[PDB]
Image (cartoon, rainbow, N blue to C red):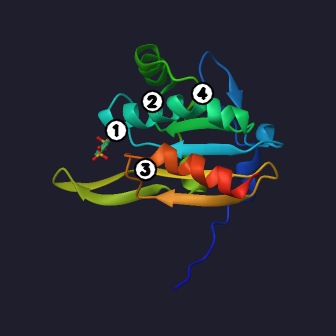
Amino acid sequence: MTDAVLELPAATFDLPLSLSGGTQTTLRAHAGHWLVIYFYPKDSTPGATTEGLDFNALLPEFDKAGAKILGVSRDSVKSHDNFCAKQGFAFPLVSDGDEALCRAFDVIKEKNMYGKQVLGIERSTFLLSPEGQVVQAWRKVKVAGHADAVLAALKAHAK
Ligand SMILES: O=S(=O)(O)c1ccc2cc(S(=O)(=O)O)ccc2c1
């Protein structure tokens, strides 16, 4: 069986991504190097912490490959700062408050939860090439062994 590849909206290229301390970046700024964008549901949860620390454990290998990592959730910069102060992630956390980046990658899903319908981030990750192409995607991500799988995919597509 086969499926259709992801098509990002043209506006995604320079969407300003809110980081900490009134600073920001863009996907455009990452051209020339591999990029891993991982979306997680909520700051300070066991799953978000484990996924982030797993990427921390592999950062030296990602760095060797010249790749950069960006974690993303809809939480505020303040929330990210707290999460950051407690776990110490060696990479930036994007505060996608207006869900612009989440919608671009189509990770916002509606699910029957807590006795009602809830819109939120479906844990997903994307690997982008130095040329800005989405090379591989992971949706409905299971945290265990995920960062390992992303690094393995990177190595398979690169050198
Ligand atoms: O993937 S888990 O099942 O660990 C998970 C993680 C964060 C969540 C956040 C919400 S939120 O809608 O309250 O932010 C709801 C369900 C969640 C499930």
The residue at which mark 4 appears reads as 92
In the rendered image, the residue lying farthest to the left is 115
The type of residue carrying mark 1 is Gly
**Could one spot residue 106 in this view of the protein?**
no
Tell me the quadrant of ligand 1. top left
**Could one spot residue 48 in this view of the protein?**
yes
Q: Earlier in the sequence, mark 3 or mark 4?
A: 4
Q: Earlier in the sequence, mark 2 or mark 3?
A: 2
The residue at which mark 2 appears reads as 53
How far is mark 2 from mark 4, CA to CA? Answer: 13 Å
Contact between labelled residues 3 and 1, with CB atoms less than 8 Å apart: yes
Instruction: Where is residue 64? Give x, y as percent.
Output: 71, 34
Q: Earlier in the sequence, mark 2 or mark 4?
A: 2
Q: Earlier in the sequence, mark 1 or mark 4?
A: 1
In this view of the protein, which residue sits in the foreground, 17 or 40?
Answer: 40
Asked if 73 appears above or below 6 in the picture, the reply is above
Contact between labelled residues 4 and 3, with CB atoms less than 8 Å apart: no
Q: So how many labels did they put on this image? A: 4
The residue at which mark 1 appears reads as 47
In the structure shown, which secondary structural element does the residue marked by tag 3 occupy?
A: loop
Nearer mark to the viewer, of 1 and 3: 1
Instruction: Where is residue 138? Give x, y as percent.
Output: 51, 58
How far is mark 3 from mark 4, CA to CA? Answer: 17 Å
How far is mark 1 from mark 4, CA to CA? Answer: 17 Å
Q: Which residue is found at the position 51% from the left and 30% from the top?
A: 57
The type of residue carrying mark 2 is Leu
Callout 3: CB less than 8 Å from ligand 1: yes
In the structure shown, which secondary structural element does the residue marked by tag 1 occupy?
A: helix
How far is mark 1 from mark 2, CA to CA? Answer: 10 Å
The residue at which mark 3 appears reads as 123
How far is mark 1 from mark 3, CA to CA? Answer: 10 Å
In the structure shown, which secondary structural element does the residue marked by tag 2 occupy?
A: helix
